[PDB]
Image (cartoon, helix red, strand yellow):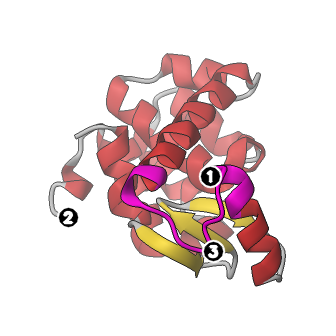
Amino acid sequence: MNIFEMLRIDEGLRLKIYKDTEGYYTIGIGHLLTKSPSLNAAKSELDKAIGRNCNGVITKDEAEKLFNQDVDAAVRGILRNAKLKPVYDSLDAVRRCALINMVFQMGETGVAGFTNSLRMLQQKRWDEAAVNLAKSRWYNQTPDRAKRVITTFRTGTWDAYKNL
């Protein structure tokens, strides 16, 4: 299993504009388009992103292209971030995928706000950190997914997705 397969399980794939759990206009594999209420603002962002008139719909290839850009930007974001990099560097390969997953969903800033949990992951206190991560809006809003990520940080294995 790798980061792409992981995120593909958590985000799903949709070829037509859709609303995310938060109500925002998204397309493809979790690619947020705009936080704006206008479906029109959305279609405009989409066309700007693809470089064509899509009229709210894209192909598999286009979805995958946006996906590769998003994972890349998520990784580079972590590496440029002063709160995030040290933690990333301290982790093993599977747990690294869990941090990338959070950054993809909630943005760098959002994850960097989990000060205490980051400190515990760094110190390798798996159980304590899993309990702390669960005390968040994140967990309360998207629990099935948060649980999967949390177990990944907890165990360092892919058990939570070997199911799926």
Percent from the top left, x then y, of residue 22?
67, 78
Instruction: Tell me, for residue 164, which label it has, or none.
Output: 2
Percent from the top left, x then y, of residue 84?
67, 29
Q: Quadrant of residue 48?
A: bottom right
Q: Label 1 crowding class (10 Å Cα cut-off): few <14, some 14-19, many 20+?
A: some
State how far apart marks 1 and 2 are (Cα). 30 Å
Which part of the image, by quadrant, shows the C terminus? Answer: bottom left
Q: Amino acid at mark 1?
A: Ile
Q: Label 3 crowding class (10 Å Cα cut-off): few <14, some 14-19, many 20+?
A: some
Q: Amino acid at mark 3?
A: Asn
Report the side of 46 relative to 151 (left or right). right
Q: Residue at x 33, y 49 (%)?
A: 6
Q: Which residue is labeled 3 in the image?
A: 55
Instruction: Tell me, for residue 50, which label it has, or none.
Output: 1
State how far apart marks 1 and 3 are (Cα). 11 Å
User: Which of the marked residues, 1 or 3, is nearer the chain's N terminus?
Assistant: 1
User: What kind of element bears circle 3?
Assistant: loop
Report the side of 58 relative to 39 (left or right). left
Asked if disc 1 and disc 3 are in contact, CB closer than 8 Å, the reply is no
Comparing 137 with 129, the one in front is 137
Q: Quadrant of residue 2?
A: top left
User: Which of the marked residues, 1 or 2, is nearer the chain's N terminus?
Assistant: 1
